[PDB]
Amino acid sequence: GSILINLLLKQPLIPGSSLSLCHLLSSSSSFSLSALREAQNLAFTGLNLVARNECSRDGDPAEGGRRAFPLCQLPGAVHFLPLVQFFIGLHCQALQDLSVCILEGFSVTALSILQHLVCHSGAVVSLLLSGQGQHPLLKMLLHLLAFSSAATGHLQASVLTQCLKVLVKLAENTSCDFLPRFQCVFQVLPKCLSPETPLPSVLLAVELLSLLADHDQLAPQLCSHSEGCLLLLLYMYITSRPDRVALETQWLQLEQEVVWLLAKLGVQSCQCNVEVVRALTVMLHRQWLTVRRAGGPPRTDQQRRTVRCLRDTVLLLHGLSQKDKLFMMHCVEVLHQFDQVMPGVSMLIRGLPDVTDCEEAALDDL
Amino acid sequence: SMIPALRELGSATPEEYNTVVQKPRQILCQFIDRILTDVNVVAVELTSVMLLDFIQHIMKSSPLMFVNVSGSHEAKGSCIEFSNWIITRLLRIAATPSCHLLHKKICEVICSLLFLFKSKSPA
């Protein structure tokens, strides 16, 4: 995209830290003062290709088939990726070793640039498509993400978020066969969900978990284990919020991503299968409270999204009512808290004109 | 047709329920084919509209006819094919200019059918 060149040359995407994309191309300071000057010259070459912007013409009409509406495949983007390797992966080595902060800032900037490239180019993804150990920058990224969750550092918090987001955005456009690669991320992703991992990383986590349920290999992974299943860590984070900031407009987002995930798992067709239902009840209440006190509809789009998660929760509990037919046995324990929320939201959903007749039958159940 | 027999599976197993229910589904189908065979034969003027209202009301009244609650996995391949035949009739209309103004009438039945499909299962 021409905007991709804009993004390339832009004030530090990351808020603050004095980051210069012009340093992502030309920074004195893997090391040894050789071939990294060459990497900088290569960044300059990508800028040269970027400028002309001949590729981003007529909305990328050439590309077709899978990954439809592909971000204009950009040769220059592939070139930028190598210098990023000198950056992100170096800290990964520092990470391998039992200062680092200076490296972490450059690494975070490099990850941001990598995110932009991955999002807006059809080439860096073609690199993902190449496959293993191919796309070695992904191996470096995967190492960092797994380690980021393990260690809780002020640098660790953000890096986790960023690596997760990169993985997720890429896995989005890729084909099913190409998602069998991202499969490796599934194992490392388990650590990310736990509260100890960054909340912003946990939200991107929920996103990637929805994506997993979209993938055929990732699904089984989401409920593969006899114990846990490797899922319900997500169910537990919405119910119990491990954030001091505890901004209300984050837990709703987590639960809403998870609810979209559940509806998607339904459409696409343990004790962990059981936690999603009770957590959906809890969220149905949570989204319910915010609207109930003020009364009437949403004076906030995020409030409208909480209402959407409400309606989706009633519909998804209905699907869950049809699911494991013996819904009541597992429901009873949280049944009082859930029964408090369900029928008032039934009234509220009847009030809105938009509510569907199918959502209405779902509502009818409870 | 035998809307009452369609309402209940009864003694029939899912596979035989497939035929027992496809029959009256096929009756609705036959009604639809002639209705949407030609936009000219029947002036859209937008009664076919009465038939569409009957189709939506029938979606509401007989979800079993639209989609089996059990799902009949193996059997449904046919129920889905039949609903797709009906929707093909509808699309032909929605393709026509004169019937493009009468689109909502074509939609009502299909939208109720989608509501029913979700009701039986979200998938």
Image (spheres, rainbow, N blue to C red):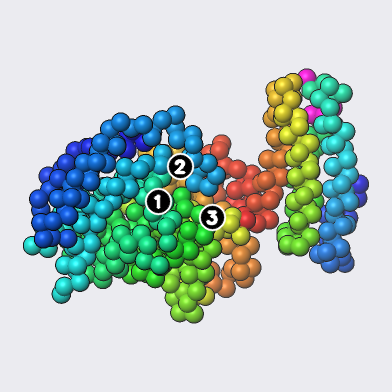
Question: What stretch of residues is rendered in magenta?
Answer: B45-49
Residue A83, label in figure: none
How far apart are the two marked residues, 2 and 3, measured between alpha carbons? 26 Å
Residue A70, label in figure: 2
Is tag 2's residue or tag 3's residue first in the polypeptide sequence? 2
Percent across and percent down for residue B56 are 75, 39
Percent across and percent down for residue A8 are 26, 40
Q: Residue at coordinates 44% horizontally, 32% vertically from top-left? A: A59
Tell me which chain the residue with mark 1 is part of. A
In the image, taking residue A190 as reference, residue A48 lies left or right, namely left
| In this view, the mark in front (3 or 1) | 1
Q: Are marks 1 and 2 in contact (CB under 8 Å)?
A: yes
The magenta stretch spans residue B46 = yes
How far apart are the two marked residues, 3 and 1, measured between alpha carbons? 28 Å
Badge 3 and badge 1 in a common chain: yes
Q: Is residue A324 visible?
A: yes
Residue at numbered disc 1: A125
Tell me which chain the residue with mark 3 is part of. A
How far apart are the two marked residues, 1 and 2, measured between alpha carbons? 10 Å
Percent across and percent down for residue A142 are 32, 64
Residue in the foreground of this view, choosing between A109 and A211: A109
Tell me the quarter of the image containing the N terminus of chain A.
top left
The magenta stretch spans residue B83 = no
* Magenta span dominant secondary structure: loop
The amino acid marked with disc number 3 is: Ala
Residue in the foreground of this view, choosing between A59 and B100: A59
Q: Residue at coordinates 61% horizontally, 65% vertically from top-left? A: A323
Residue at numbered disc 3: A263
Badge 2 and badge 3 in a common chain: yes
Residue in the foreground of this view, choosing between A146 and A262: A146
The amino acid marked with disc number 1 is: Val
Callout 3 crowding tier (Cα within 10 Å): few <14, some 14–19, many ≥20: some
